[PDB]
Amino acid sequence: FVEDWDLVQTLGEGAGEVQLAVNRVTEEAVAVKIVDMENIKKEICINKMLNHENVVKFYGHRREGNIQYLFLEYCSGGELFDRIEPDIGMPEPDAQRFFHQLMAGVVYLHGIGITHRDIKPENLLLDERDNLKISDFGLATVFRYNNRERLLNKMCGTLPYVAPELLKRREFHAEPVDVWSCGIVLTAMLAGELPWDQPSDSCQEYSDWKEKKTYLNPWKKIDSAPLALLHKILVENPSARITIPDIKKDRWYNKPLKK
Ligand SMILES: Cn1cc(-c2cnn3c(N)c(Br)c([C@@H]4CCC[C@H](N)C4)nc23)cn1
């Protein structure tokens, strides 16, 4: 009976659906991604490579006909998105802890040559202890193989989170794009709002940021220390943008915080 699972509820939709399943014998819970049914093949393949505390674990996949069944780590705390109070954000110490965990997960992925490509609060899930877990590898790809980097050219992601070079350049490096989206996530956690619809020349809010008008929202709501880190992350030129090893040296990143 240990292979029997009960589908107890729908966790959400994407894009098929994701259901919560409980083992009839052990009562273990697992998220099941159901796809009706090339893209799915890649998602499973990348998933098989993943083994990190801040990345959703992959348990396997069953194929009952035309429907694909991805068995993944269940995150009972739901989406980080739901911990962000609109127009407020969340307490700075909470935002810092989630940011630390997000960087740990991203460093791990980059170390194995994988880029997520769609980092945002809806994809960052929380377990029963509020530990952050990067989810959904349907848009993920290999950017380093046999120690040789491959440039990306495919448009993908979510506009408010996408780095400016995606929209402007034919090819671009993978890592700075994920760094940028993490900076937008940090902004959202500390301000409860996204800074711009997209980082384009045509976007007034993006121009304001480039002109350093930090007396305007959402910047005005962010303390000087984390704001200084955002100044280093949200840099238009990806070659000048701060790297993760340097984010780890940042003053705010290393500031002891307590609620
Ligand atoms: C791909 N994947 C999902 C899971 C997953 C695990 N827990 N979980 C919870 N609690 C919710 Br709410 C969602 C919803 C499922 C619909 C999309 C939402 N972003 C997240 N997905 C999940 C693990 N891997």
Image (spheres, rainbow, N blue to C red):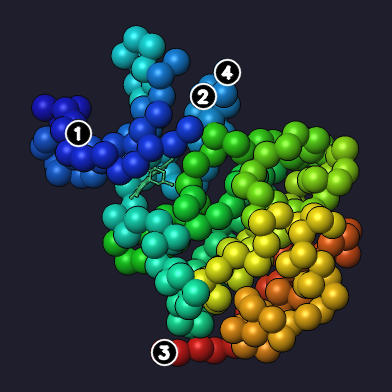
Residue 178 % position (x, y): 68, 53
**Which amino acid, by three-letter code, is at mark 1?**
Leu
Q: CA distance from mark 1 to mark 2?
A: 21 Å
- Residue, disc 1: 7
Instruction: Determine the residue positioned at 32% across, 66% down.
Output: 129
Q: Are marks 2 and 4 in contact (CB under 8 Å)?
A: yes
How many C-alpha atoms fall within 10 Å of the one at disc 1: few (<14), some, or many (≥20)? Answer: some
Contact between labelled residues 4 and 1, with CB atoms less than 8 Å apart: no
Please state if 22 lies on the left or on the right of 250 as rendered. left
Ligand 1 has an atom within 8 Å of the beta carbon of the residue at disc 3:
no
Report the Cα–Cα distance between label 2 and label 4. 5 Å
x and y, in percent, of residue 103 in the image: 60, 63
Residue 212 visible here = yes
Q: Earlier in the sequence, mark 1 or mark 4?
A: 1
Q: Is residue 118 left or right of residue 204?
A: left
Q: Position of residue 49 (x, y in %)?
A: 55, 37
Dot 4 corresponds to which residue?
38
Q: At which x and y percent is residue 51?
A: 49, 46
Whether the residues at callouts 3 and 2 have beta carbons within 8 Å, the answer is: no
Residues under labels 4 and 3: Cα distance?
47 Å
Asked if 21 appears above or below 1 in the picture, the reply is below
Question: Is residue 147 shown left or right of residue 222?
Answer: right
Which label number is shown at residue 259?
3
Location of residue 150 by image quarter: top right
Nearer to me, 198 or 190: 198
x 40%, y 56%: residue: 79
Q: Secondary structure at mark 1?
A: strand
Badge 3 amino acid = Lys
Query: Label 2: which residue?
Result: 40
